[PDB]
Length: 335
Ligand SMILES: NS(=O)(=O)c1ccc(Cc2c(-c3ccc(F)c(-c4ccc(Oc5[nH]nnc5C(=O)O)cc4)c3)nn(-c3nc(C(=O)O)cs3)c2CC2CC2)cc1F
Ligand SMILES: Cc1cc2nc3c(=O)[nH]c(=O)nc-3n(C[C@H](O)[C@H](O)[C@H](O)COP(=O)(O)O)c2cc1C
Image (tube, rainbow, N blue to C red; front, side, top):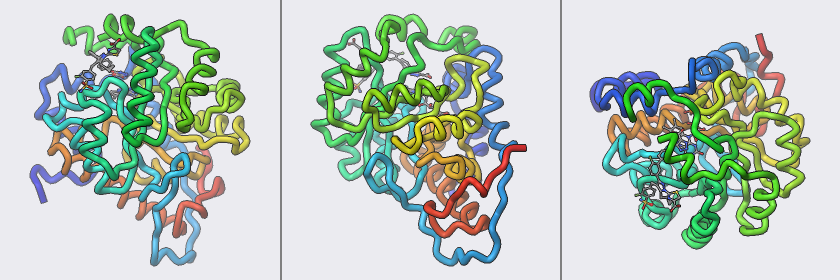
């Protein structure tokens, strides 16, 4: 009952725009270039129509599932978002605490405003994963992985779509990064560097930012454990498809050999249901978490995750799904 009265994820965004400095809100909101993919990440979900089954018995809903062999309370997890401390003083420590309370997983940015150890201490019982860039400096890359293994993180999400930073026009206009990303991130990396990381760690490895069937198959062939279908929140290459539109081609391409996840434009419970109906194991949210932080730190993130949880529960119930095992491709049809 905290004010203003926010009852959906778009209310959290509207609140954030009213309290964040322009250049911070713009950094978090922006897509790349004309933001074609940004609009489509959202619009594409509306074109997938639901076909609810009546009279299935939805008295008891169970949202529980597993990610990479680890139980979660719901198929709705926190994605890596850099610079959470610009949204709230507690930053990633607030986030992990909310994930611990919800029983869901947090993917930590490889350049978070909090250390791998600090986040493990704030959230010792939270399911925690590390998002990894392969830096030009492979010694710091290796150290992050070792620190993740040591601090009880359960997987590496290696981001492969950012050899350079996307062109976000508001960040250029605000004089808000591309030059710094280009100093640290290695744009030379290939499947050879994936072989290296696959040998470096026995943690589960997900390739984050695949949009092609052939690349997904290359990821399976290299012993990777998951695909995160991502266009990096439409902040990298503008004019790529919406993740919900390429998800089915990627699911088909991997023939059940690895878990397939989605991010990009998840705002509502029906977005989660549509993604699972098309074969995603779970979805990740980026921006909604930041809007949560901007509203009220830990409680704001908990609020956003609880809103998505309960929207998802209702969408499951109204569609005749008592649990995620019964969510099938006949629930959806593109229009
Ligand atoms: N609390 S803490 O001590 O752990 C802490 C961690 C991180 C930072 C910030 C940081 C930046 C750093 C700077 C300035 C920045 F502006 C950024 C940055 C912020 C947001 C970005 O946004 C995105 N990344 N991926 N996608 C996006 C997007 O916006 O879509 C990118 C870069 C990073 N680099 N950097 C690197 N150093 C090396 C190297 O060779 O030694 C390799 S990485 C680090 C340390 C990190 C360990 C590696 C400070 C600490 F205090
Ligand atoms: C503000 C912000 C910071 C981000 N930082 C990172 C990052 O550090 N590492 C990474 O792999 N992806 C990063 N991403 C991409 C997200 O992990 C994720 O793909 C995206 O937010 C999903 O789309 P959504 O914002 O529509 O939920 C970032 C995205 C945003 C919006």
